[PDB]
Amino acid sequence: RSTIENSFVGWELEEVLLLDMSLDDGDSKIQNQLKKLQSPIILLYCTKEEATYIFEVANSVGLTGYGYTWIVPSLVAGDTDTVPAEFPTGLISVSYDEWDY
Amino acid sequence: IGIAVILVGTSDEVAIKDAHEKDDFHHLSVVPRVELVAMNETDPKSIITRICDLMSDRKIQGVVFADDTDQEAIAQILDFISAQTLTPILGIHGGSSMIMADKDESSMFFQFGPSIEQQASVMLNIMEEYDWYIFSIVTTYFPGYQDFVNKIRSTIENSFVGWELEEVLLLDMSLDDGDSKIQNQLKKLQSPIILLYCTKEEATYIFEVANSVGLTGYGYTWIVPSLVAGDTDTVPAEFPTGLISVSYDEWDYGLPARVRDGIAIITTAASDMLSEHSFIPEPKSSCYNTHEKRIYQSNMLNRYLINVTFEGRNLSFSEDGYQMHPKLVIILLNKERKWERVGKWKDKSLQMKYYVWPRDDHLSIVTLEEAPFVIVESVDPLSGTCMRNTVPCQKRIGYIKKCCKGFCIDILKKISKSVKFTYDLYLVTNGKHGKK
Amino acid sequence: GTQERVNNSNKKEWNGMMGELLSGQADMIVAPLTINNERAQYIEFSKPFKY
Amino acid sequence: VNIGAVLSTRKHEQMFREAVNQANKRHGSWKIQLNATSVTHKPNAIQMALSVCEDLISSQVYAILVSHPPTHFTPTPVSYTAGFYRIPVLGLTTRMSIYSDKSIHLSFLRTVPPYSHQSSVWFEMMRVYSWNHIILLVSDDHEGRAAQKRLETLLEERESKAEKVLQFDPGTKNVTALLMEAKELEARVIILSASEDDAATVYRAAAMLNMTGSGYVWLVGEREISGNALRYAPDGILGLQLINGKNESAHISDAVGVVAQAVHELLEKENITDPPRGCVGNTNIWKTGPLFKRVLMSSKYADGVTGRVEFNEDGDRKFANYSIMNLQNRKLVQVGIYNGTHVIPNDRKIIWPGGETEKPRGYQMSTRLKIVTIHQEPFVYVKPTLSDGTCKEEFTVNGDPVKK
Ligand SMILES: *[C@@H]1O[C@H](CO)[C@@H](O)[C@H](O)[C@H]1NC(C)=O
Ligand SMILES: [Mg+2]
Ligand SMILES: [Mg+2]
Ligand SMILES: [Mg+2]
Ligand SMILES: [Mg+2]
Ligand SMILES: [Mg+2]
């Protein structure tokens, strides 16, 4: 938000969601919240297991097909060797330099 | 002329018998000797046996069939029997009333019901009534979808009004693991109207998938034919609230009335056959010796059975089997899920009860004719709908709809586009601007 | 040529040279015919010979 | 389990029982036994329906096989009777294409492709011969409409449709008017699809109008080169025939094998209900046809006596083999084999109607054009002619022969 506000280029910050996973039987709430998503670019911040569960919840609303981009920090993508099948193709991530260092 | 009225299931035989001897046949010369029979079994074998015996021991030309079940096999069996025995048959109620296309050649079986094209025309009329021009089409791989799409296309183009028809889907419900493709392609839909067409189970599955995707919300409307609705009493929980459908008249068209107006058709048709050709042979023996029983051509009565203008708006019967002037109604799913009636359609006339279609980001706006700020001097062009730069305005007291334009109208259009809110415009009745 | 309605049911139909070409009584139109979007959706125009 | 069959001849019943015994021996590992019940076809449709209701449904037959003899004959009564209880019915000698409708004929399968699929074959003949200009002469019946729709869809898939689809009313011999209308269509390839009598009348009309000469190509199906029509068929007609469409023994064996294979998979689940056995007062769906017809359609036979067994989404034979023959010297000779995806010609030479020994282009371009003009003074001066037959000759300022 701070970076967006102090800039002369428009972003419009279409939506900001806050999913709750602690409570059980919350799949319906997560699905309902995920419906109100239309931006071509989506930023995600969660753990690997939470990310996999969210992606599984996704692919039903239709947020994993062509025309959608997902960018996640290094936290979501842990051991690069182990890639869960729930991760959509074309996902982008930022990692530390550990192959050239 | 011998006419057998067959009832299957539970029905008021006394009422039908009383109504039978209530028609004035003085204008014609038919002598409609009516024989009423009632049963409970609906097995093909029993039906064929009863039809055979009755025709044998009775000089019955026409047959009227009624039922309370929902099996199309009854209609198919009736059509096959009529084709084989060359004896007219009229299905009124129950499964026999279900409309089936591609009847057997040289068949004399007719049913009380509309076709897919008529339902599509009714849907288009409903859409144009409330100024719904942006819509899509969603049809699966079921017989009749091609005819539905072709009829919709034929109309949209042959019109001066402006339609959109954003896209048409197929949604093949046969590929394994195809749910992903269905959900992905269903997300592209954006038109308020979808105009679905499929069976009941397919309709329920598609409705569940759409609800998961995000459709069936506050700003989406679904219109389906009579096939999707099926039985009114049984309403699956997957059907979204506010779903529109077009059905036959089953509330104000009772069985005693349905049985009537059909015997009159046969009597007229018969007369015409006799009067026009100085004779009307009825040589049927029981069911058999097709060469011996049905040796002469009975197609003469066909040309008269399809034109009977006694009381039902010419009661025209299409060569396919359906009637060209049916009585259809519009049903909407309310909060209680009871399929309440809304409007009626007859002779290309729509009589709706809602003038605004009551259903967030929707509010009413009041205007008044004045200087170029707001101009209402526009009723309707040759197209019959508002112009490009005008907006509907319901002048209350009567609720005639006119076209509004001007400085204030353009300002309102821009404001609504920018803030993304929906509005309905109507003029003020009492007072000009306001005074305490 | 232009697109007009009829006293009968609303059926689209052309008139004049456009109608004659669409019906099939003619194979080509050689005259001062302007190129516009309305007429370009049914027939094909060649490169302009006079701007 | 009980398997019912309606066959024209008793010997066919013996073959069916032998096939059922063979299936039992092949699938004898399981504890499921299949019993064979056979009935003879009758001239009367009502009698056939009564017989199927009495001696067939009362035996709780899971599936019923039907084979219409060439000399009612159509399996419509059996299909209608079985559709009430949703019992699958497998037909062998039936290609009317009416039974392919799911709404009309419920729970119906066929071991032979319908006539409509023939259109697909024609598409191949239009891809290896460079024939982009064709005219259809289908009838006004359901079969003609279905064939025309299939051909139109196939052409649309190639983004190239036909030009004329003029039809004719069945039973009207006079087709000379339509032939004359189609004569001046700048097209030579003609596709016909009608009954034997209609084919004969069309051939007579074409011959009387000299439309069967050089430069004309005729394509037909299977019914246009058989019976009386074959007697009136002009030389140079490319007909199609089914490799295995008349030998009902192989079809019976394949159907018995497929049904036996499907039954074992069907019984490997729960919530299985036996079919009705009384069919006297009961008026409810058997509750077994569903999940059974789907299993039958999805059951791909490993290898039969006539080839791989497969069914489309509409429940019809898939990947069939056709023989393309050419009528030369009043003698049909095979000239090609359609292996279901492509057409392979043999070493024989195809004799065209003109005997050119080379495939005609099949399309001629008219060199005469009709032009419509309007009266515009700067661009079009129109003046009355003289009394001789031509308007006065005029010269420009430079004395040039102004052309009118
Ligand atoms: C049919 O012939 C074509 C021609 O090469 C071949 O590619 C194909 O494998 C053959 N079999 C089938 C089932 O298409
Ligand atoms: Mg490391
Ligand atoms: Mg039809
Ligand atoms: Mg159109
Ligand atoms: Mg009732
Ligand atoms: Mg029809």
Image (spheres, coloured by chain):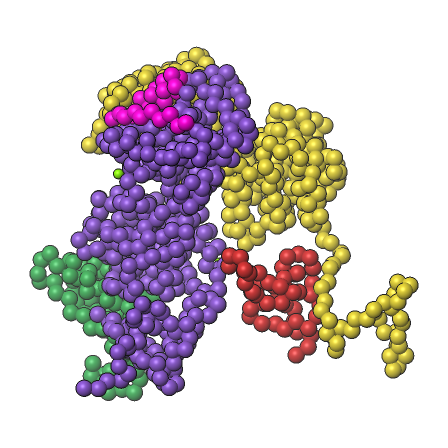
Chain colours: A green, B purple, C red, D yellow
Task: Say which quarter of the image contains residue D252.
Answer: top left
Q: Point out residue B196 in the picture as x, y percentages from the top left corner.
A: 34, 53
Of B48 and A24, the residue lying toward us? B48
Q: Point out residue D40 in the picture as x, y percentages from the top left corner.
A: 42, 15
The quarter of the image holding the N terminus of chain D is top left
Q: Is residue D187 left or right of residue B317?
A: right
The quarter of the image holding the C terminus of chain D is bottom right
Q: Residue furthest left?
A: A23
Whether B384 is drawn above or below D155: the answer is: below
- Is residue D124 inside the magenta stretch? no
Of D291 and D347, the residue lying toward us? D291
Q: Residue at x 30, y 79 (%)?
A: B367
Q: Is residue D282 left or right of residue B388?
A: left
Task: Say which quarter of the image contains residue B243.
Answer: bottom left
Q: Is residue B154 left or right of residue B356?
A: right
Q: What residue range appears in magenta?
A: B31-58
Q: Point out residue C29 in the picture as x, y percentages from the top left corner.
A: 69, 65
Q: Residue at x 31, y 22 (%)?
A: B46
Is there any visible trace of residue D1 in the rendered image? no
Q: Residue at x 38, y 16 (%)?
A: B57
Q: Point out residue B191 in the picture as x, y percentages from the top left corner.
A: 35, 63
Is there any visible trace of residue A96 in the rendered image? yes
Of B54 and B85, the residue lying toward us? B54
Q: Residue at x 71, y 69 (%)?
A: D374
- Is residue B46 inside the magenta stretch? yes
Q: Is residue B151 left or right of residue B71?
A: right
Task: Say which quarter of the image contains residue B131.
Answer: bottom left
